[PDB]
Image 1 (cartoon, each protein chain N blue to C red):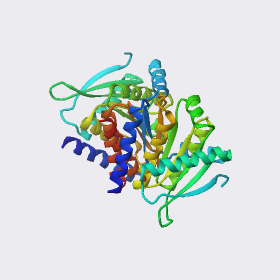
Image 2 (cartoon, rainbow over the protein chains, first blue to last red; image 1 turned 60 degrees about the horizontal axis):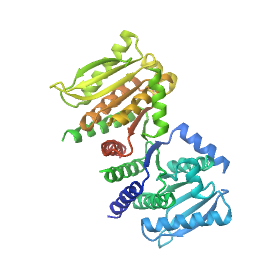
Image 3 (cartoon, rainbow over the protein chains, first blue to last red; image 1 turned 45 degrees about the horizontal axis):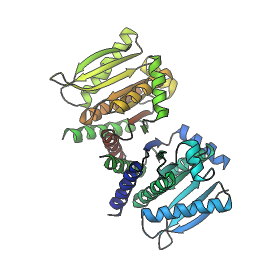
Image 4 (cartoon, rainbow over the protein chains, first blue to last red; image 1 turned 90 degrees about the horizontal axis):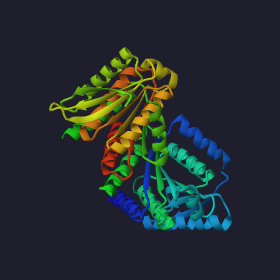
Length: 206
Length: 206
């Protein structure tokens, strides 16, 4: 089904990133008092963030890659530190959000910090608060980061498009990409997402 | 098969810990220059560690719980900061290792640090170096920690017995347990273990 196809896209993008010469570092972090406090401290440093809405009728890696490229182009044109994307389906219903946070040109952040991109992923609003705040923390450390809030096939297709963006930005220079799934410890949806991402990663390494 | 039964034990112990009043915090960390350096710094602070060998003919949560209790009793009797267990099958072949690191009585570490136990799990020798070093780091911060090195059903049964130990030590006082799976980013065995633990955790939350 759609979730299986989106997971296969994640596996294919993980394999492709490694074949191009970079390591994928996968981390899973719980929402805890320590991670919540870090996220809140970073969010306090940045409602001030611009929003735009993109229409993605179906969950595909190619569509998320193109939306992320559009968001980076807008950040460059406006000189902004971050942009919040609302992602909607063909009926206009929201199927995800992506906060994109840049510290400068992406080629330069990759070289200065030694990481091409940090991709945070969450499904629940509680995980997403932490994912968004940690993306801002990464930006304030000098790196390019994004935080995807979505579920099921949309979350996986978003992750696959973000890995494709990381691969394109790396240009075979060998910098790693870090993927961080954030989950509220009690939320089975967050747990299901983490399990699906880990399974897709296991399949990429076989 | 054995792996499925061991995973079901993990799921049952996760459910039981939560029903007793504590949160399970699950983290997955990659081996990276940062985590390797932290692990090496802690290992340098502690070949000096005592070894004992326990015979566990089959991968069961009850047997790992009892072995861990025996290890804690030995630490108390000898006044030692850590003990390395070799775990062997009925033919004497090694099926895992567990480094157990205590900062004092386990009831007191749970109260002082706000965490009852930190359980690190790895399959590959590279993940296990980091798991062992991070267990020592936890001990030096005042907490009780253990690092399991094993694969398949043995790793999962070890994790299930460690969760049972955490539940017993918590005595319903509500402190969380932290489980940390450590993987070398390229190693499919480490990835397979992380995927199996995440799936068992998703099943516990449903």
